[PDB]
Length: 117
Length: 71
Image (cartoon, rainbow over all chains, first blue to last red; front, side):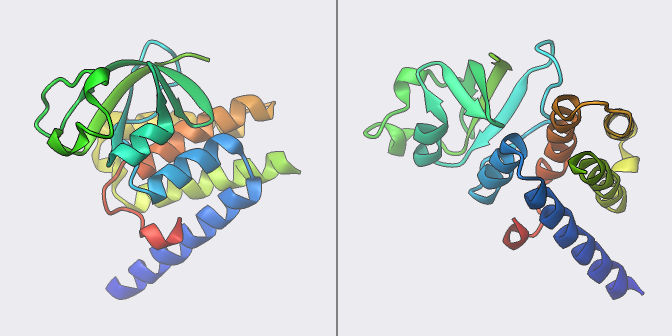
């Protein structure tokens, strides 16, 4: 039943997201969608502003979609960006992230933020 | 009605995590169980859905854990 445990896991996961999609919650729907595009949490999404959010940004297109100024839009909520680092774990300024300069950046980027609402 | 659905889903979500051997991580599992518990005890959708976001994020944070085609 080694292969059977896999089928069960697969079946359970299909039902899981089907149930989630039925709930039709904006926050859940957002993180699911982002995850489908490769935009995923590095760590558990913080319950309180004490803990910090860390999210993987695969490409500039995702960044442009989810980031405006210092504001990061995720889980149908706003987040104040604390820091951004590249795939080399080197600090990246927000002003460095642009259409022109993105090929020189090391992707993916990791955004650190606190809940703004 | 929507409340029973989200509570039912949270049980499934913890089970999916359990079969992914999250119990091997003591602190993370404790977080998941706590979130799962609070969702079941949740008296309003605002509290329930917020905890569900965090619980689901654990699953989505695990590389290769979920087939991307199911999303």
